[PDB]
Image (cartoon, rainbow over all chains, first blue to last red; front, side, top):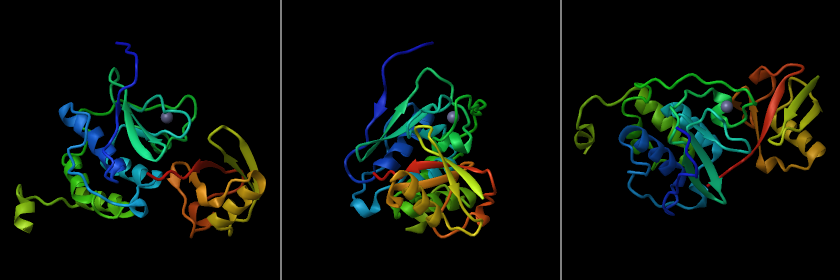
Length: 164
Length: 75
Ligand SMILES: [Zn+2]
């Protein structure tokens, strides 16, 4: 069904806006709640997140999301935008998620770009948990954190409590 | 050899380079042609985000290759 208007999630002003954006994408995918469940985490300019960081992270978590430079990828369900210096994210509600090629994710794709349907069991189980474990790292290390977690994830249901 | 660089607005820059040339060299050349400071340049090749340290050789960028020029975003 065609819809009109723009539906945007704007993170808090804590300094972790990019990571909140990814968290919110996943939170809507999993629970229908387009907002960050990550606890707010303060940091200054030198720990801001780049388009590089966010792109790597999107690929690790396997999100139907692009970083919008100029043209928005028509196949991206989630559009990440730098609004001044505040990472925000739009969502196309009336649209099935599509698994995006790398050029589509990065936002340098050409007219005619194609992407197949995102599989229902397509979001890595414990993606949001991986992000939650990683985000408070330095931003340039967060994607490595996510990748490490997802690749070799702690199997114990209360592993966090164990680690304490 | 010749490579092409495509800006976000769909401009196509043509560069003379060597396989040995570092990503930093390429950025400096883009500056000479376009007045875009390397500070705010990021080069993509087939989705792969290039890094300052490495050469064109390392990324398998041969004659006629097309790179995508992108503006560095921080938030
Ligand atoms: Zn695309």
